[PDB]
Image 1 (cartoon, helix red, strand yellow):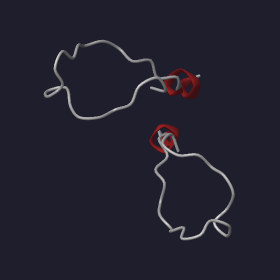
Image 2: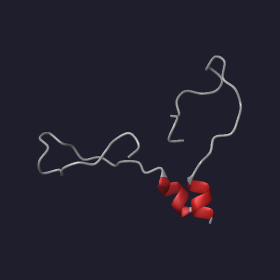
Image 3: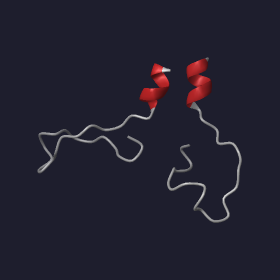
Image 4: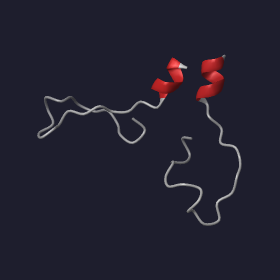
Length: 31
Length: 31
């Protein structure tokens, strides 16, 4: 999440693809 | 916070205004 920013939506962006984005907060808070 | 940075205080900056700054960790911490 620190290497990218959220904007728009996946239904308008051209050439968008599907994958996973690592969130460092989840492993740290759940541990 | 990700879109801004902390420096100085509110008594030095001229023309500063008061508003709430969103914290991305707030929803995660409460979860």
